[PDB]
Amino acid sequence: MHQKYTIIVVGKDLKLVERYVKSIVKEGRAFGISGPCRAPVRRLTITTRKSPCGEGTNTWHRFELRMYKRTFWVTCGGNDISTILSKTVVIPGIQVTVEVEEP
Amino acid sequence: GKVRTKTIKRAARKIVENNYESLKPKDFQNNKAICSKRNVAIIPSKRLRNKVAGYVTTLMNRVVKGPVHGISLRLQEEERE
Amino acid sequence: IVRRDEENVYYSKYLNDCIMEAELHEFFSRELVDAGYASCSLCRTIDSICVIIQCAEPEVVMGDNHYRLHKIEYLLAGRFMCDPKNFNIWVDKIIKRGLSAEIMVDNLRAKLEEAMPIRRAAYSIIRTAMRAGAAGCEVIVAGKLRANKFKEGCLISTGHPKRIFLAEATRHIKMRQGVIGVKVRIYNPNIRGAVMPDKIEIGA
Amino acid sequence: MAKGNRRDLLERNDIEVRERDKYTVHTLGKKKNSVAVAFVKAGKGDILVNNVPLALVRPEILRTKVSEPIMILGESLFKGLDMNIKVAGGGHVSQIYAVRQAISRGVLASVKDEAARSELRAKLVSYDRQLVVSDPRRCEAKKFGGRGARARRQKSYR
RNA sequence: ACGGAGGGGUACCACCAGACGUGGAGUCUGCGGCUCAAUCUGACCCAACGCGCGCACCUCACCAGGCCCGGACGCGCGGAGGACCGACAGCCGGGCGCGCUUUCGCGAUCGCGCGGGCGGUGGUGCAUGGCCGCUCCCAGCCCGUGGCGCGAGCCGUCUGCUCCAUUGCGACAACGAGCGAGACCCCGGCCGCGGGCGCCGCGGGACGGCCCGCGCGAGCGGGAGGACGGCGGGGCGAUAGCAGGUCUGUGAUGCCCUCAGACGCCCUGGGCCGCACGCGCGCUACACUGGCGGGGCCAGCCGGCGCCCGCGAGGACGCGCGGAGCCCCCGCCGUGGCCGGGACCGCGGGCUGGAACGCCCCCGCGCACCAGGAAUGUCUUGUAGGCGCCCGCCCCCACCGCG
């Protein structure tokens, strides 16, 4: 019936994470699913010496890993748990693009 | 970047010799637009397109004032006698 | 306006699964070499993970009715403490084997350990790649034999395009006299129909 | 504390709604990490800053700087306009300069005529051009070789 | 390759013009030397010395002492008529059934030898892989055919003009390709669309384009208009090479040394901090362009708060809520090593931890230091300099490093 459900999309790659939302909004064309809030990027950072022994000019690697995430809490109870499964099946299967649904 | 690499020059020369009737020199908008056409020529990157177009306009006005060697203009009609 | 320790679970939940995988890559490399494993992935299911793999010889990985694959299936479950059955591995196949570095390097390593010397193996590998539609390869063998290189055609080695077009791999060989460091690099400028920059065409 | 690009500041939701609408013109001005938002409505004439009279803004010595857009021109048009500026960012001086830029841009828009607008543009830009066009330069990063953007840690060759 | 040989170029890791400094004191730290039982080791011009990511126990190799086999698997002999393994009580032992003194318990999970292992911050980095450093903040490197030489080799790959650039124009026994450079990726400044819990996704825009001078030429000088004008800051990084560093990062490893009084693993202590002295990167100052008190006030990487005790550091409760120094204003001090300076030292109150040698706050004492010789380092716009704020290793602590 109505559950005030939530949709959350978490991933690293900007390309898929932006293409997947387009399909989701297509699927929510008639169920009223609307714009997603795009959270500030969680740019994780790490630094390390490039030399295992610490010889020579002190240099530093700088790797970082971003965590883009979007939220489609629009459905809420607007949709039924019957098609919430339908919401979760017609969507494409991307290898890594974690998602979770809560009320 | 002021000195233009070889690729820019060669491709620009090809474009001028091929599409000459529709490249009005001294403007950077018309020539850019025409180079945008895939029937004309293809540029993968924006900056490269702008660079090529600029060199094409400079070559085209240099030619309209005084045509060059290596670029075929079919000017025989006024020099065939 | 918002609380920063709620989304931390989702962020930390995605990071754990990333590491959960690399261990899989290491283990497969230590085990399913026989089938020339290439790469893996993951897809957190409702009650399991839908890991799919890519190995040139699919038959070797699975057994009678996938029996040994089933054997492996339970193993992972205990290690990650997930419910068995729900585990559902998948097996794939690679078509253009002369376009992947890892299968070639593994075959080359095995060949080298077949008493045959570096030259024949390296030239066999480069021929196999070039006949498989590659702009060029490069074989380097370093150890107690210095460095004896072999190369055929044009490769790029600098710039952003390297990480996507050029694919490299490395290995180590434990030979009686010492260790034979061997690596391989292949440059395919037509991968996934991507246009390499400064590559132009003009028409009539 | 405020970033400057917060949705609340940009839309000035702090003001009550029934008074929000009466403000028509919208203007912007910035210098370095500082964003000043100005809303204008024609009126008897008055200015404000972060809920403060324009006169009593405390660099004190820079009062003429915050008021230059006015004494450059005549008070004739400034008489008929009232502003409620809201600023937030880094540094007192940066806030000052952003505020004067916003004042200039806002008064320029409300003229409603293009020719007189161009004339005012010519008058104002003749004086300090950075009263209409923003200033681009911004702080740069620091490399690990040294302990500053360009300075390097002292080296001992011996 | 070199030249105290010539000619073209080039760079604040070079100079001109300047700026800010170090070497003079006190102090943090590392490096040699001395000392001890040990004060564990690697590296020594550029290219060793806040670097091998914070040492009370572990970390940890080193010193004083002590538990255990945690000896797989095979072969030969023995063994439930009993192989091996634990223990209340009393002494010696830092303590432990560690050892001894009586006597109970357990039951093949094996015991002795021979083959054969695993393990080890133990050695050779001059046996090696991998990763970095340097040559290199470079602009250079080669292929097929062809030609010249008996040949090693040469031309291609430039004694011309341009570019920061083997970047380009124009020639030539050479013709035609390739790598590196560029393009490329991240970030920021302007604009548009869309969406929006939280400002975040997709695109336009700047190209030596316009005008004027020159130059065949590529390209140089000046002026505009514009958010931005001519390599804006970073990432990537060619060929070949070094006896550069790393066996003490690893189920990376060859060969040596150790393997039942152990270099294995573990436990209690101590040490790595010990100090007549030499110097390397830093921190605090020598004051009026200042010190003290009261008050007003604005940042970003990003971010957690209320009440009550306590001078303060801190402490007991309960919930989800929130940002600074410089600076400006008013007064005191008045050139006196003084109210500049806060090293050193004596009572005391707290925190972490099993354990303070560790760290904070309060009262008291108040060292050198009056701008630092020979010498030497860095720097061109939001830059130097000044001011503060978060992360790293972390039970506590930042004068360090990344931002």
Image (tube, coloured by chain):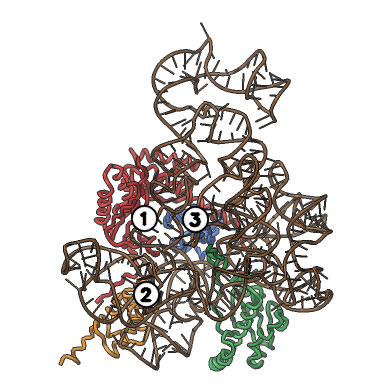
Residue bearing the label numbered 3: A55
Q: Chain D: give its colour.
A: green
Residue C181, numbered circle: none
Where residue C115 appears, as percent x and y from the top left, is 28, 42
The N terminus of chain B is located in which quarter?
bottom left
Q: Name the residue type under label 2.
A: Leu
Neighbour tally class for label 3: few under 14, some 14-19, many 20 plus, Cα within 10 Å: few
Which chain is represented by brown in the image?
E
Where residue A7 appears, as percent x and y from the top left, is 52, 58
Q: Which chain carries label 2?
A: B
Are the residues flagged by discs 1 and 3 from a single subunit? no
Q: Is residue B48 left or right of residue A53?
A: left
* Nearest-to-viewer mark from 2 and 1: 1
Between the C-alphas of marks 1 and 3, the distance is 27 Å
Which chain is represented by red in the image?
C
User: Would you identify the image quadrant in which residue C158 lies?
Assistant: bottom left
The C terminus of chain B is located in which quarter?
bottom left
Where residue E293 appears, as percent x and y from the top left, is 80, 69
Residue bearing the label numbered 2: B48
